[PDB]
Image (cartoon, grey):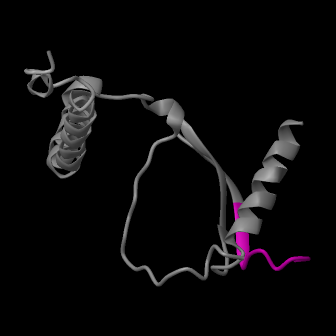
Amino acid sequence: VEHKLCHSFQTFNTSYSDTGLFGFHFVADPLSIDDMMFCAQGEWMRLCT
Amino acid sequence: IHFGNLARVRHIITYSLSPFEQRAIPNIFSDALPNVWRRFSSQVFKVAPPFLGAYLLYSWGTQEFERLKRKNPADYENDQ
């Protein structure tokens, strides 16, 4: 919100029998993709630490 | 802000793998070396020539210069 990074974003933990996908998906304007991904990954790193 | 204002690109998919899922120097023989030769081959005849032609000129002038130091007996065949 503070930087108008994306129109929307979501975390997801899709599970499967023997595997799965853990991540996130955001929708943004062509010119803020970078800052968004940056802040996002940051939070992930903020999680492990 | 140089990334994003570059150019109008449409319909191009690219696939790449994390560096840790692949080899650093793959197919050294099957693929690598052959191209190294391919490339060497391609250029050899554009480059090498003028270099070789220079070498000659070097060798020629270099020796011809020495020859001009040695004496010619035909200058003393009567100097008794």
**Residue at image x 26%, y 38%?**
B58
Q: Please say whether residue B11 is one of the residues in the magenta stretch.
A: no
Placement of B14 over or under B37, stated as above or below = below
In this view of the protein, which residue sits in the foreground, B14 or B2?
B2
Q: Is residue A18 visible?
A: no
Q: Position of residue A42 (x, y in %)?
A: 82, 51
Q: Position of residue B75 (x, y in %)?
A: 14, 28
Placement of A22 over or under B32, stated as above or below = below
Quadrant for the N terminus of chain A in the image? bottom right
Q: Please say whether residue A9 is one of the residues in the magenta stretch.
A: yes
Query: On the picture, is A30 further left or further right than B24?
Result: right
Query: On the picture, is B6 further left or further right than B61?
Result: right
In this view of the protein, which residue sits in the foreground, B31 or B37?
B37
For residue A9, what is the image quadrant? bottom right
Placement of A31 over or under B46, stated as above or below = below
Placement of A30 over or under B27, stated as above or below = below
**Residue at image x 20%, y 28%?**
B30
Query: Mainly helix, strand or loop, the magenta region?
Result: loop
In this view of the protein, which residue sits in the foreground, B21 or A13?
B21
> Which residue extends farthest front?
B80
Region rendered in magenta: A1-10
For residue B61, what is the image quadrant? top left
Q: Is residue B20 visible?
A: yes
Quadrant for the C terminus of chain A in the image? top right
Q: Position of residue B7 (x, y in %)?
A: 50, 82
**Residue at image x 68%, y 70%?**
A33
In this view of the protein, which residue sits in the foreground, B58 or B18?
B58
Q: Position of residue A26 (x, y in %)?
A: 67, 67
Q: How many marks?
A: 0
**Residue at image x 82%, y 43%?**
A45
